[PDB]
Amino acid sequence: ISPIFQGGSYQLNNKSIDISSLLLDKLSGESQTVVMKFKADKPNSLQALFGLSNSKAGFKNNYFSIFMRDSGEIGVEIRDAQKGINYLFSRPASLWGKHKGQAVENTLVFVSDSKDKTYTMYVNGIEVFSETVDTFLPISNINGIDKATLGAVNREGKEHYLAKGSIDEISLFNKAISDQEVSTIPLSNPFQLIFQSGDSTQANYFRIPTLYTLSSGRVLSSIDARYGGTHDSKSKINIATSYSDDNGKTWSEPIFAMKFNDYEEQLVYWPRDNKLKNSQISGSASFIDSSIVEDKKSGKTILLADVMPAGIGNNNANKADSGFKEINGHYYLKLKKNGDNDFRYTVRENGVVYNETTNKPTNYTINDKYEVLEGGKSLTVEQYSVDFDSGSLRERHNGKQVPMNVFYKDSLFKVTPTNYIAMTTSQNRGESWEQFKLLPPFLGEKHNGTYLCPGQGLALKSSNRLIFATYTSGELTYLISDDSGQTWKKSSASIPFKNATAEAQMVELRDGVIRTFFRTTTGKIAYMTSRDSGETWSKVSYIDGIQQTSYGTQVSAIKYSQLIDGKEAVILSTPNSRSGRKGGQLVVGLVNKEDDSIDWKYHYGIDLPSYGYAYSAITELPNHHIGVLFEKYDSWSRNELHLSNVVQYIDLEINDLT
Ligand SMILES: O=S(=O)(O)[C@]1(CNC2CCCCC2)C[C@@H](O)[C@@H](O)C1
C-alpha cells in the first residue's frame, strides 16, 4: 500500500511542528506503520521524535510517542489513562549519530499490529524489539487524541520531550506491514553486519570481534557466537569466522572455528527484565575470547581461544589447577571418571586413557575431537536445549545423541573444571578449521591457564616468530612459537597489577621492536616495549590523552603500512571515556624514530561521545583503508545486556581520521 501521510525535511530545533491538520483525519483502523528517516547528531537527553496526544487538561497521560535518549536508546510509549494502559517498550543502543563526522540518516520502522497484538520496532534494518500484549492499544485509539506532533509530545498544551535533530522523511500507513515488506524499505546505513542474528551460527548474540588481514588479501574475522544472551562463560558460546575477499565489501556466511555440541545451537530471545536477565546457561561447555595470526612459513592461519568445561567460566574456574599432571617433564590432561571423587586418570600419547592409581592403560581412548571412545567405539551423550517456557530458564535433554566429549557435563570422563587455551589451524584461509588442540600449561602444574588476549596475534616481519599475548595475575604471558605453532614457550612480563583483566594487543614498530598496549585498572591504557622480538620486556608506561573507566576496555592496535605526515603511524581503537564504554575513537599516533616515543596526534570520533563503543577489532585492509568491527554498545552496563546486531563493521580512509 501507499502511505496515508508523507512529509519531509522537518527541522527539529527545540520547537515542535504541528501536523495535526495533515495527519489526524487520515488515521483509520487499529493497525499502523510509521516509517521515519531522521538525523540526531546532537540529541537532547530525552526527546520525542513523533507524538500523537490528547493535549487537553487532565489527560497528560493519554499519548503515543516515539522517543530516543542521548545514549542511543530508542522506544515508544503508548498510554491511555481511561483504559489503565501505560506501555513503554524500548531498546538501548539502537541508533547511529555521526559517521565520518556527517550526521547519519537513521531509518526507523514502527509496526503496530492489532491482529497479532504486537508492537515491533526496526532501526537501520535491525529489529530492536517485538512485544506482544494481552490488551492491545491501537496508537490512534487513545482517548481524545487531538494532536499529531513532530519533535515533541503536546501534553496539556505544553511541549514535552523537545527534540533536536531533523526528520528527512516520515510516512504513515493504515496497515501493519509484514516483516517482508519492511525488508524492502531502502536504508542509509553507515555500517555492515558480518555476523548477525539468524545467520549460520544460529546465535542471537555476538561479542569479542577480531579482524586480521591475510597475505592473499583475504580479510578474516572471528567472534564469540554467544547463545545464552551476551553473558561471558559459563554459557554456550562457540567461535565463528567469516572472511571477505573484496576489501570488506561482502562477507562469507560464517562457519565454526571451535564448537561444542553438548547443547543445541539455539537462537533464543534472552530476557532483559530485572528478574530474569542474569539467567545463564549453566551446564554447557564453551569457548571464549579468540585471537588470529597468519604464519608466513607454513601459510597456515592459526586461531586460539579459551576453552571452558561445562558450567565453567572465569568466575568459578579452579585457580590453583592447570588441569594437567606433570610426568618426567611432560604434561598430560587429567580426567575424573563417573563416581570417582578424585582425578585418577590421564590422557597420554595417542589419546590413551591411563589410570594413575593403577598405573595401567584402559580400554578408553580420547580421539582428536576430545571425544571418548571405548575400545574404538564412539560413546555418546544426550544433547540439551534451553527454554523459558516455564517462566525461568530450563536446561533439558532433547532426545538427540552427540559424541561424548571430555568437556561435557554428561561425559563418563571429565576434565578439571578450569580454563584452558586451545589452538586450531586452517590450511585454506578460513574456509575450514581443524579440530582444536589444547595448549600445555606454561606456569606450572598448579596454576590455571592464562587468559587469551582477544584480537590479533603478531607475526614478526623479519622472521618466522609468532606471538600471542595472554594475561594472568601479575603479568602478561606472551606465548611464542618459531615453528608454525607446533611448540610454544612463554615470555613473562610483570605488570604492577594483581588480578587485572590486562587484555593486550601488539604492534611491531620496526624490525624486532614490539610495543604492547594493554587495559588496566587505572583509567589509562598502558604499554611496554620489547626490542628482542619478545624475549624481554620493559617497565610499564601509560598513555595520556585517552581515558578509560576504572574497569577498562580491550584496546585494539595496528601498525599502519603507509607514512602519515611523513612518519610511521600506529592506530589505536578504544572507547575514550572515564564513565562507561562509549565515545569510541581511533587514535592515530606518529612514531618519533629518535626514541620510539609516540605522539598521539589525531583522535577520530567513531560516533557520538555518548553512544556505545566497547571491544573492537581494527585492521588495515589490503587497499590501505581501515576496517573496524566493534561492539556498538556498552558491554559493561547491566542495562544493555542481550542486544542483537550491535557488533557492526565500518570502512574508513586515513583522510577521514585526520
Ligand atoms: O603486517 S602484518 O602483521 O602481517 C598485518 C597485515 N599487513 C598488511 C600489509 C599490507 C596492507 C594490508 C595489511 C597487520 C596486522 O594487523 C594483521 O592484519 C596482519
Image: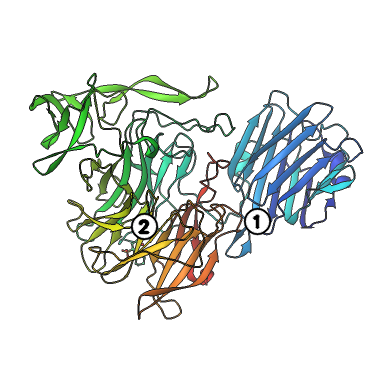
Which quarter of the picture shows residue 570?
A: bottom left
Question: Does mark 2's beta carbon lie closer than 8 Å to ligand 1?
Answer: no
Residue 168, which numbered label? none
Instruction: Name which residue lies at 49% across and 61% down.
Output: 651
For disc 2, the marked residue is 496
Q: Is residue 161 above or below residue 459?
A: above
Question: Neighbour class for label 1 at 10 Å: few (<14), some, many (≥20)?
Answer: many
Q: Nearer the viewer, residue 428 or 11?
A: 11
Name which of mark 2 and mark 1 comes first in the sequence.
1
Residue that lies at the very extreme toward the right in this rendered image: 57
Q: Is residue 605 above or below residue 404?
A: below
Q: Is mark 1 within 8 Å of ligand 1?
A: no
Give the color scheme: rainbow, by chain, secondary structure or one colour.
rainbow
Asked whether disc 2 touches disc 1, contact meaning CB atoms under 8 Å apart, the reply is no
Give left or right: position of 29 versus 469.
right
Image spot of residue 438 (x, y percent): 23, 42
Give the crowd class for mark 2: few <14, some 14-19, many >=20 residues within 10 Å. few
Secondary structure category for the residue under label 2: loop
The spot of residue 368 in percent (x, y) is 20, 36
Disc 1 target residue: 105
- Residue drawn where x is 34% and y is 51% of the image: 291
Quarter of the image for the N terminus: give it.
Answer: top right
User: In screen coordinates, is 113 left or right of 594?
Assistant: right
Looking at the picture, does residue 521 appear above or below residue 285?
below
Identify residue type, mark 1.
Glu
Q: Quadrant of ligand 1?
A: bottom left
Mark 2 or mark 1, whichever is nearer to me: 2
Q: Position of residue 70 (x, y in %)?
A: 66, 52
What's under tag 2, amino acid-wise? Pro
